[PDB]
Amino acid sequence: ALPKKYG
Amino acid sequence: ERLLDELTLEGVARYMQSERCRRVICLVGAGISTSAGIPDFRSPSTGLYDNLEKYHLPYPEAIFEISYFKKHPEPFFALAKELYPGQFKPTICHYFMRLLKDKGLLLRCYTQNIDTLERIAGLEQEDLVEAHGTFYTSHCVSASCRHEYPLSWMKEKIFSEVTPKCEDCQSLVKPDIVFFGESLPARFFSCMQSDFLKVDLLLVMGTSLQVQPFASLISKAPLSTPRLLINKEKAGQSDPFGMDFDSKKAYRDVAWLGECDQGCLALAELLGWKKELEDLVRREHASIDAQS
Ligand SMILES: NC(=O)c1ccc[n+]([C@@H]2O[C@H](COP(=O)([O-])OP(=O)(O)OC[C@H]3O[C@@H](n4cnc5c(N)ncnc54)[C@H](O)[C@@H]3O)[C@@H](O)[C@H]2O)c1
Ligand SMILES: [Zn+2]
């Protein structure tokens, strides 16, 4: 999986 | 050898009208749409993470996290109805990027926004990396179906307060946004691996640069590329516990602190584009009013 959105 | 003759908006404008500045990348966030009536996160009280009590979430951030959405999509769609704007009118800042496009300067606009205002302003799919997706299209979530639905369909479902279900298979239909915890689109990584090879200017507008991996984009340009931040607050600086505006080593980063619309107006004026920008915004807003 591609890198995930994180705050 | 530094490319800006001075670390000011006036220096950036002189550089933009030099032969060296041919390819501009914009990096934008929620601050470019607050004047269009879409709340950001940073604003006190009006940020989206405030005024959520009514939804009874395990924690405030859950409303934008994919794990929670999967189990309980109803709070998100209720918030969407509350925030949905009466009209979609792009801002002066959006139309400044339209001018960059019209004038052959815009290599890419990387946006964190999902509100579609870049497209309404006339940026084409080719011009955009919608890094966190978009509300413009939605899809059934079932892997074997994936039926697509337009915003007009999703809007009716949101306002009727009916959880959107696919007409072919009755699975949930989800706006094409990237929730926290979801993978960004492949287009983001493929564009990021080509666009920053010979970019001449980064224009960073209306973002706190706190969400990853989008925030890492400012570090992908060559070390000589000037970076102009137009934002209410200084952002992108290294945390004392990146952008270098103020040190003795500073050589290429400029912070213009204020409203994005006013900063883009100021830059346009230095470039000789002020009348062009005013005329474009007034004509586009009048057309949006007339089509309603
Ligand atoms: N419009 C949208 O699509 C929208 C709205 C809210 C949040 N988000 C999502 O949540 C995250 C928000 O991150 P972000 O950095 O974009 O937003 P943010 O709220 O974290 O930061 C916005 C930044 O813009 C500044 N700002 C606000 N209004 C401004 C104005 N008119 N002129 C100049 N500066 C202004 C704020 O001071 C702040 O630094 C992203 O993941 C994004 O996808 C999107
Ligand atoms: Zn389906």
Image (cartoon, rainbow, N blue to C red):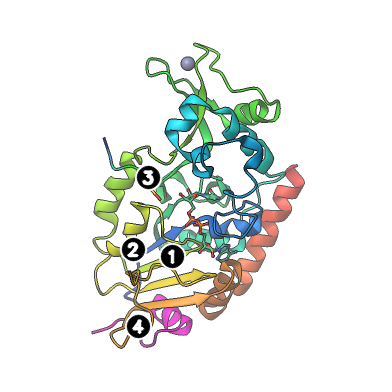
Indicate yes or no: mark 3 CB to ligand 1 under 8 Å.
Answer: yes
Q: Are marks 1 and 2 in contact (CB under 8 Å)?
A: yes
The alpha-carbon separation of the residues under discs 2 and 3 comes to: 16 Å
Ranked by sequence position, the earlier of labels 2 and 4 is 4
Q: Which residues are magenta?
A: B1-16
Q: Nearer the viewer, residue A5 or B59?
A: B59
The alpha-carbon separation of the residues under discs 2 and 4 comes to: 17 Å
Type of amino acid under label 4: Leu
Give the residue at mark 4.
B4
Ranked by sequence position, the earlier of labels 1 and 2 is 1
Q: Are marks 2 and 4 on the same chain?
A: yes
The alpha-carbon separation of the residues under discs 3 and 1 comes to: 19 Å
The quarter of the displayed image where residue B178 is located: top left
Q: Secondary structure at mark 2?
A: helix
Q: Residues within 10 Å of mark 1 (few under 14, many from 20)?
A: many
Image quadrant in which the C terminus of chain B is located: top right
Give the residue at mark 2.
B218
Give the residue at mark 3.
A5
Count of numbered labels shown in the rendering:
4
Which numbered marker is on residue B204? Answer: 1
Q: Residues within 10 Å of mark 2 (few under 14, many from 20)?
A: some
The percent position of residue B244, horizontal first and vertical second, equals 34, 77
